[PDB]
Amino acid sequence: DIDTAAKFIGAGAATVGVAGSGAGIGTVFGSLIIGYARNPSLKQQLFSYAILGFALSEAMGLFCLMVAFLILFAM
Amino acid sequence: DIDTAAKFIGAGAATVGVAGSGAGIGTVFGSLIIGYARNPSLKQQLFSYAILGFALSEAMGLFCLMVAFLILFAM
Amino acid sequence: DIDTAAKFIGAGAATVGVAGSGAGIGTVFGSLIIGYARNPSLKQQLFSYAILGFALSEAMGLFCLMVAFLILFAM
Amino acid sequence: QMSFTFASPTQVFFNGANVRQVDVPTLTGAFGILAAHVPTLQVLRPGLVVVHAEDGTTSKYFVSSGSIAVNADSSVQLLAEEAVTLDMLDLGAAKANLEKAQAELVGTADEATRAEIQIRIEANEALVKALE
Amino acid sequence: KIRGILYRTHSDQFLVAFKEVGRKPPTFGDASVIALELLNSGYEFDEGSIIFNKFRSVISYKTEEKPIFSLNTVASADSMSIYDDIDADVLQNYQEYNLANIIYYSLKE
Amino acid sequence: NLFASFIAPTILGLPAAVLIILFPPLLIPTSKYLINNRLITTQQWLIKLTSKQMMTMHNTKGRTWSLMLVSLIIFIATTNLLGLLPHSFTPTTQLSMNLAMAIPLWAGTVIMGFRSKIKNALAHFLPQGTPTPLIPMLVIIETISLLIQPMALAVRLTANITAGHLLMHLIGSATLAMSTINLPSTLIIFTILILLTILEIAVALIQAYVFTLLVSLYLHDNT
Amino acid sequence: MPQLNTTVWPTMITPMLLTLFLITQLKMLNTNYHLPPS
Amino acid sequence: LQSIIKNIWIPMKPYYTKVYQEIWIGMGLMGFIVYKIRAAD
Amino acid sequence: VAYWRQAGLSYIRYSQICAKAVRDALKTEFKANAEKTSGSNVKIV
């Protein structure tokens, strides 16, 4: 078969989109260190921006993992 | 066939474009934490840019998830 | 027909260059937050640079989608 | 919106004035200061200070040390220990004393008394570039 | 004069003293010197006040004391968190200069 | 033919891989005296500087491992450094050995985080200032990464000593090929091998300090 | 990859455990730092 | 076979019993992995 | 942390040399007047 074959390169190359959410979570939690080394009295408000940036960058990672698991098992 | 096979490799290699919409959403919310910890008196106006930047970098990510769902479902 | 099936790969792989622009727009609108949180009385002229940067990177993100539409249909 | 205050120990240039921009030579690198600039506080190094009046017309003084402090209410207090307008400095003695400073460093090897030469070197190096 | 008065009671509680104050009008060169030996003294002072005669008119003056803060109190105050580009060195250079000012402003009053 | 330096060494039918794993401790002599020789004076100083580094960040229960996490940076930093010798078989390029140093020190670290203090170890999976409405996604990360930390250690060290030896062995074969060709080029390929050997010396120590720091950081998060 | 030849794994596991846990540590227990005197 | 108690186990007594007790619980996990990996090969 | 701060100096000593340098570059019309309006006379016991 050539469908079951290509559906592995597809679902295998679709999951490179996680390379984005790898360096998006590294910047959010990287600049949180620089945002805290400057104004440590905002530790509760900063960390609530890091979790917002960690959940919105990773959500773009899931949208890729969601597609790789869509062109593999769903259809 | 050979087409329905390649349609999965093209739709997979196209949704890698989200990897640039995950490093942007990371840098925007990475500067919202740095910019707001420097001048917390501008919380409402700095956050009004981190929503524009979030929506404008994620608009280039949709342009890839769209051309993926064009080779995959339309043609 | 190995060529018509190849167009779905060259056109689905050219559109991953858009992931460059989408990462150079989060840098621009993440530098507009760091540069406005410092000297906010320049909001007018800064935003006329965060548009020259947005419209010069996102032009490179269109040169990729220009070849993606040059292989998929113009051949 | 800006409340400038530029004052030597013996002279006052501005006081509560409303200028739109100042360009000071801070030790951590120069920066320009418009209204609502982020609150900071620094210490100057030898260099110019350009003051942009509301009319867009400038004014250029050569501070030598001190401390600028932008505040939360857009007030600025620039205090220079010796702030002489460029119409009072000469180019010949700056370049000459810079040479007398540079030539005296190589003859010196102690960490302390050579550190006082580099500060005299950069103070004169910042002089030649201010005049012309 | 201020030494020769308190030299009797509190003489060991005395870091350093100065001369030649009064003959010539006090200049910043005098306030800058006094600030140096207040730092080249090995006294880890954690709080300070300078007492001078505030001039109001030809008829009357008042005595006054101005507070002098060290680094660990101006760097730890949570009201200094708004001040940008600040590290514990650019505060030291700013606290060492503001010692020569409050002495100069005192010598003129 | 290329991975020859990683096959289990045997001489005369004897598994010589045991006289190579037991040798590192032979280079660390000890003495009860008060003023000894230069070797034990420099070594007892390194062990002092090292133990003050990994162990200072721990509480009183974490400092009971101050014999393990110091006798481990001494065994990995001496096995790697004894691998840079010519033809040497360094047993840290083995996924077997590395998986045997990684799993116990890791399992014995989360167990004491699950057999005791468990109610506190349940709070590292959920960071402090975390809003709720997307928690059912974060639970996957903090567990599946925990379940793969023991394999991160053993492969971060295997793939860094293996690839370091493979590179030095290839660039070495390059200089051999261009030896009978333009020789002023051999001297530029060789000076790349020298800068690469100074790198593989540093990465021989760094890969020992990072291994025993990540085992330390796991411990610090469970004691 | 010769690392995957699992027939020689017990030849690498046991002499390691006999070194990381018994021989290297024993030599550390002999390295003692006495407290300084008055 | 003496001093295998004195030199070899007397020192390691407070560690092999109390401190490394959970290490062995992990070392059993490891042995189960190694045999299983060799079982499927 | 600048080099002079590593060399033991203080910003007062830094400012005394930078201000001396500016006056040393003043022109003779102003150099005499500027030096006495900022010269030092105090002395330590």
Image (cartoon, coloured by chain):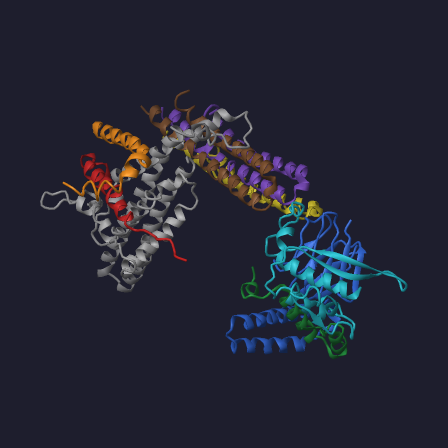
Chain colours: A brown, B purple, C yellow, D blue, E cyan, G red, H orange, I green
x, y (%) of residue C22?
53, 39
Q: Nearer the viewer, residue H22 or D84?
A: H22
Residue I28 horizontal side relative to residue B54, left or right: right
Question: In the rendered image of this protein, does residue B35 appear above or below residue H22?
Answer: below
Residue D79 horizontal side relative to residue F55, left or right: right
x, y (%) of residue B33?
59, 40
Hey, which residue is sitting farthest left in the picture?
F12
Question: In the rendered image of this protein, does residue B7 appear above or below residue D123?
Answer: above
Q: Nearer the viewer, residue G31 or B1?
A: G31
- The residue sitting at 24% across, 30% down in the picture is H37
Q: Nearer the viewer, residue B64 or H23?
A: H23
x, y (%) of residue G25?
27, 45
Hey, which residue is sitting farthest top in the picture?
A74
Q: Quadrant of the N terminus of chain E?
A: bottom right
x, y (%) of residue E13?
66, 63
| Residue D83 visible to an observer of this rendering | yes
| Residue G1 visible to an observer of this rendering | no
Q: Nearer the viewer, residue I9 or D16?
A: I9
- The residue sitting at 34% across, 34% down in the picture is F108
How many numbered dots are placed on residues in this image?
0
